[PDB]
Every structure is written in structure tokens, then in C-alpha cells.
Image 1 (cartoon, helix red, strand yellow):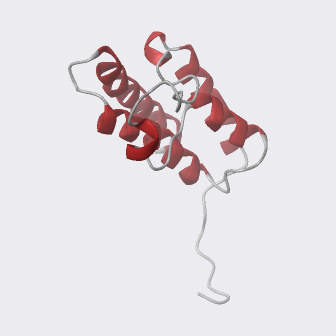
Image 2 (tube, rainbow, N blue to C red; image 1 turned 30 degrees about the horizontal axis):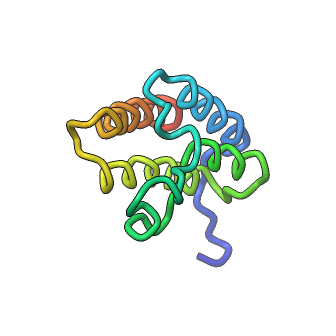
Length: 116
């Protein structure tokens, strides 16, 4: 509260770390469904069904232009990518499995990098 400051973690390297994690996402072999926005005029259903589309290149743009206030908002966009993927694609499919793989890959890096 007012004049009662909680000790807070050193956040000064968050930008460089999130960038590093994102680079590793982008270079993963199963990253191909998520590198670019889904084509709204070539993929039937997507615009109507998925209310907040997100992909790595959009994340990369927001990261490069100061549009994430904190590392938690960045992780929200990354998870949004895989949450959209689950919504639209069957777990069995190539894209669906890519999504589960990439989420697992992200969440470990997130823990390793930031949670102590």
C-alpha cells in the first residue's frame, strides 16, 4: 500500500530474456503454424470463431516496439497463440499437435528462465 513497498524482482533484463525465448520459439521445427498471422480470408471460420488472433511475428512486433508493459503480458500473448490453436484444431492434427508441443516447450523455458 501507500509508502509500503514490497521488494520486487529485478526486471531489467526481462526484455532481452523474453526476446531470447521468442527466438527459440521461432526456430523450433514445429513453429511453422504460428510464425505468421492465420490468413483470415483463406481459412474459413477463423475470423468469426477466434476473437483475438495472435502469432509469433505479431508478438515479435509488439516486443520490438514496447507494447508489452511487463513479462506477464508477453506470456499472455504467447499462451493465446496456443489457446487459439487448441480452439480451432484437433489434438490429433499436425497443427494441433504442433501447438501442444510448442506450449510445453514454452512453459519449460518460462519456468527455467524466470521462476528462480
